[PDB]
C-alpha cells in the first residue's frame, strides 16, 4: 500500500523551497553549505562575518535567498563547537529550529541531515534526533477554543535504509510522548476513568495487545480495597486497565509497568487548598506515561513481554468518601490506615502493583505524579526514583540516560520502613508526614513490591511545566513514556 510517512530519507533535494542547515563554529564552510555559499555569491560568509547568521549553539537565523536560486527560506541553526557537540545537542538544535518553523506555519521542510552529523553523532542518530525533536517541538495543545507541518525530508549521502530507520524510531518516541501530553492536558470532565479505558481499548485494537478492563464488581469480588477505597466518594465508576504485549515466544521475564490513573484529585476529605487543586486533571500523568509507552512498544514490536496495569478513578468528596483514620484491606491483604485522603495515589498503586505481581510481572516500574515532596527534593526537572533492587535500577537509570529524561534515586532505609510500618491500627501508614515526603510514598509502594525487583518514579514535578520550551508547550510534558519504552528495548533478565 506504500503509505507515506511524515519523515522521509532521500539522497536528493527534491523540495528546496524550505531548508534547514546546521552550522558548526568552524571558520570555513564545507560540504553542501560551501556550495550554497558560492551559489549565493559569498552572502552566507558575509552574514556569518557580520553576525546576522550565527553558528553559536541554538542561534536560529532565517535567510531568504534570491528567487533565481530554487530556494525561498533557509533556517540556519547554530550548533556551537564541533568538539563539544553531542547527540543531546542535536535534539536541542532540532527542537529550537522546528519551534521557529512551527511558528512560521510551514508545511514542508528539507533538512540537510549531513550538516548535523559528526564523529559522535552519526547519520542514523541525527535522524532519530530530528523526528523525535521535531514531533515534540511542533506539538499543539488540543484545545476547545472556537498550518500543520506534514513533510520533513532528511536529505543525506548516507545509507537511506538506516537513516529512515532512525527517522522511524525518533518518530515513534515523539508520537507516544505527544499522546501522553494529550491524555494529560485533557480537562477532567473530558477524561474519566471510563474515557481512559476506551483509549486503552483503542490502543489494544490498533496494536493487537490483550486488553482487560476490570469493573467495580470484579474489584469487589477480587478484594481490591485500595482502588475501591479511593473510588467510594465517586459517582464516576472505577477501572483497572490491563494491557498484555507478548513479544517473546514464552510469557516469562514479564516487565510490569504500573501507572497512577487518578483522573481528578480533589484531595478528598483531607481537602486541598484553592491554589493546589487547579491542574489536578494531571494526576493521571503516570497512566499517560505507560499508555504513551505502550504506543511506542506497539510501533517498534520489541522482543519483550510487558504487562501494563493502570488503576484509575477520581478522588472526590461525598457522603461515602473514604475518611481519615479508616482502615482498609488492600488487594495484597495488607491493611492500611488512611491518615490522609490526599495520599490516595499510593493506595491505588498498591493494588496495581499487587495485581501486576499476581499476573506474572517479574520486574516492576510504577509511574505516578505522587508527592509535592519530590518537587521540594529535586525540583521540576528531575524525576525522583526509588528502588528495592540496585541491579534493576541500573537498567532503569541507563534507559533514562538514553531517553534523555533525567532521573535521581532517593534512599529507602530501614528507618524509612519503620515510619511507614508505624500505624497504631494497621500494617501500613499511608501518610507519615512531610519529612522525606517522597520517600515515604516510595517506601509504602515497595512493601507491595515485596521481593520483585522494582522501581518507583515520582513525576509530580516533571509531568507538567509552567512555561513552553524548545521541546513543547506549557502544560503536560509526556515525561517517562520514552524511558519506559527504551527500558523495554534494553531490558535483559537476571
Ligand atoms: Ni518527494
Ligand atoms: Zn492526592
Ligand atoms: Zn494524587
Image (cartoon, rainbow, N blue to C red):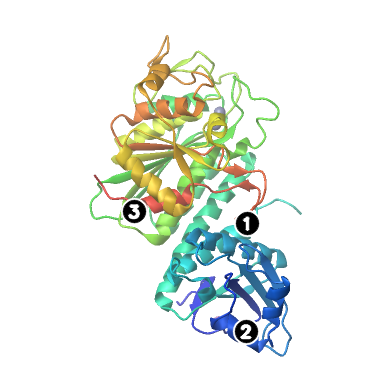
Residue most extreme to the top? 424
* Circle 1 crowding by C-alpha within 10 Å: few under 14, some 14–19, many from 20: many
Q: Which residue is mark 2?
A: 36
Please give the residue where the numbered disc 3 appears in the rendered image. Answer: 490
Side of 379 where 482 appears, left or right: left
Between the C-alphas of marks 3 and 1, the distance is 28 Å
Asked where in the image residue 342 lies, by quadrant, the reply is top right
The CA span between labels 2 and 3 is 41 Å
Between disc 1 and disc 2, whose residue precedes? 2
Residue 258, position in %: x, y?
A: 42, 39
Query: Looking at the image, which residue is at 57% across and 48% down?
Result: 477
Q: Earlier in the sequence, mark 3 or mark 1?
A: 1
Residues at marks 1 and 2, CA–CA distance in whole angstroms: 27 Å
Q: Is 190 situated left or right of 217 in this image?
A: right
Q: Give residue 308's position: percent from left, percent from top.
A: 39, 44
Which quarter of the figure is the N terminus placed in? bottom left
Foreground pick, 480 / 261: 480
Q: Residue placed at 36% from the left, 26% from the top?
A: 447
Circles 3 and 1: CB atoms closer than 8 Å: no
Q: Quadrant of ligand 2?
A: top right
Front residue of 433/40: it is: 40
Q: Nearer the viewer, residue 43 or 187?
A: 43
Q: State the SS at label 3.
A: helix
Q: Which residue is mark 1?
A: 470
Q: Residue at x 54, y 70 (%)?
A: 6
Amino acid at each position: 500500500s506504500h503509505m507515506a510517512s511524515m519523515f522521509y530519507a532521500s539522497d536528493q533535494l527534491r523540495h528546496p523551497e524550505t531548508l534547514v542547515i546546521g552550522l558548526f563554529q568552524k571558520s570555513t564552510l564545507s560540504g553542501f553549505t560551501k556550495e550554497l555559499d558560492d551559489k549565493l555569491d559569498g552572502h552566507l560568509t558575509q552574514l556569518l562575518k557580520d553576525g546576522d547568521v550565527s553558528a553559536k549553539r541554538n542561534r536560529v537565523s532565517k535567510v531568504y535567498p534570491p528567487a533565481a536560486t530554487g530556494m525561498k527560506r533557509i533556517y540556519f541553526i547554530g550548533m556551537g563547537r564541533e568538539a563539544d557537540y553531542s547527540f543531546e545537542d542535536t535534539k536541542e538544535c532540532f527542537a529550537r529550529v522546528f519551534q521557529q518553523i512551527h511558528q512560521d506555519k510551514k508545511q514542508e521542510v528539507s533538512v540537510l541531515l549531513d550538516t548535523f552529523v559528526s564523529g559522535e553523532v552519526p547519520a542514523a542518530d541525527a535522524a532519530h534526533a530530528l523526528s523525535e525533536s521535531c514531533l515534540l517541538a511542533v506539538y499543539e495543545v488540543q484545545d476547545y477554543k472556537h498550518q500543520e507541518l506534514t513533510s520533513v525530508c532528511a536529505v543525506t549521502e548516507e545509507d537511506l535504509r538506516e537513516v529512515q530507520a532512525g527517522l522511524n524510531v525518533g518518530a515513534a518516541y515523539g508520537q507516544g510522548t505527544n499522546s501522553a501530553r494529550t491524555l494529560v492536558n485533557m480537562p477532567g470532565n473530558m477524561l474519566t476513568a471510563t474515557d481512559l479505558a476506551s483509549y486503552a481499548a483503542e490502543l489494544a485494537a490498533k496494536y493487537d495487545f490483550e486488553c482487560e478492563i476490570l469493573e467495580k464488581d470484579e474489584m469487589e469480588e477480587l478484594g481490591m480495597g485500595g482502588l475501591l477505597a479511593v473510588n467510594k466518594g465517586s459517582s464516576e465508576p472505577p477501572k483497572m486497565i490491563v494491557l498484555k504485549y507478548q513479544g517473546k515466544d514464552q510469557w516469562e521475564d514479564v516487565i510490569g509497568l504500573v501507572g497512577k490513573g487518578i483522573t481528578f484529585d480533589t484531595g478528598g476529605y483531607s481537602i486541598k487548598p484553592k491554589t493546589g487543586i487547579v491542574g489536578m486533571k494531571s494526576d493521571m500523568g503516570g497512566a499517560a506515561s505507560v499508555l504513551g509507552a505502550m504506543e511506542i512498544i506497539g510501533e517498534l514490536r520489541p522482543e519483550q513481554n510487558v504487562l501494563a496495569v493502570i488503576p484509575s478513578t477520581d478522588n472526590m468528596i461525598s457522603s461515602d468518601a473514604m475518611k481519615p483514620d479508616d482502615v482498609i484491606v488492600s488487594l495484597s491483604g495488607k491493611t492500611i490506615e488512611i491518615l490522609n485522603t490526599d495520599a490516595e495515589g499510593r493506595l491505588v498503586l498498591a493494588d496495581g502493583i499487587t495485581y501486576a505481581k499476581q499476573h506474572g510481572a517479574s520486574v516492576l516500574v510504577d509511574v505516578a505524579t505522587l508527592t509535592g515532596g519530590v518537587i521540594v527534593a529535586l525540583g521540576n526537572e528531575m524525576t525522583g526514583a526509588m528502588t528495592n533492587n540496585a541491579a534493576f535500577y541500573e537498567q532503569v537509570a541507563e534507559s533514562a540516560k538514553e531517553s534523555g529524561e533525567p532521573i535521581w534515586q532517593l534512599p529507602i532505609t530501614e528507618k524509612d520502613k519503620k515510619r511507614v510500618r508505624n500505624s497504631q491500627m494497621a500494617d501500613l501508614n499511608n501518610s507519615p508526614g512531610r519529612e522525606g515526603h517522597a520517600i515515604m510514598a516510595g517506601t509504602f509502594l515497595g512493601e507491595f513490591a515485596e521481593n520483585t525487583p522494582w522501581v518507583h518514579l515520582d513525576i509530580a514535578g516533571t509531568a507538567t511545566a509552567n512555561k513552553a520550551t524548545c521541546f513543547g508547550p506549557a502544560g503536560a510534558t509526556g515525561v517517562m513514556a520514552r524511558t519506559l519504552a527504551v527500558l523495554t528495548e534494553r531490558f535483559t533478565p537476571e
